[PDB]
Length: 173
Ligand code: HEM
Image (cartoon, rainbow, N blue to C red; front, side, top):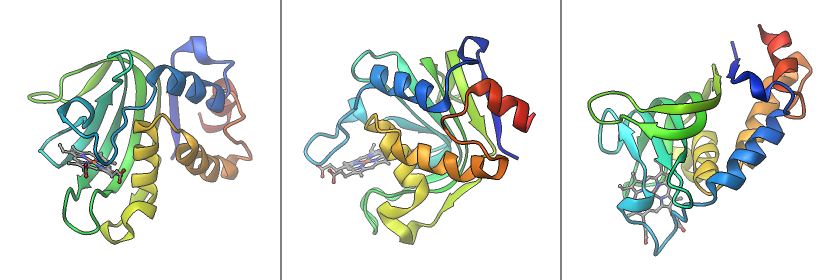
């Protein structure tokens, strides 16, 4: 039940092409040991350290953003420390993050969204869990874990992240 939604200007991009463009614009928020403040922590909708969405905007341009949707919880200092886990269904990418407190986060100039990812990870997997790898990678402007996960999904259709959005649309829709 994987789905893709995209601005039609991306029809002829591969998934890999689009993610490379987004990652080059987003940069890296440097959410690392010695470097974490409110500026680069992002935030959850629905709670302080858990909720139905997690979102963050670029510290390089202040506008490029992603929103992850699902049921997500971050352990902060509980073991295994600094682990994001749960059920991740959707990822939306674009410019202009809005909302997040009394209403859900959304994106004002959206490019692409993936839904039906059905990725699931347990607290005890710590940093090797697929949800943590995907989202922490995106915060660091590294799309590798997401690309590996999407290849796992797309193999059922005989596609991969080198397929264009219009190719994926014809296969899943
Ligand atoms: C939900 C998405 C998040 C993920 C995937 C994530 C992941 C991580 C990772 C992997 C580290 C360790 C970096 C290293 O060892 O170099 C870390 C550190 C840290 N994170 Fe997060 N984090 C997230 C959100 C947050 C939030 C919302 C807060 C608090 C508002 C937070 C507070 C911290 C702190 C205080 C540190 C430790 C910095 C230090 O030891 O100097 N993180 N996080």
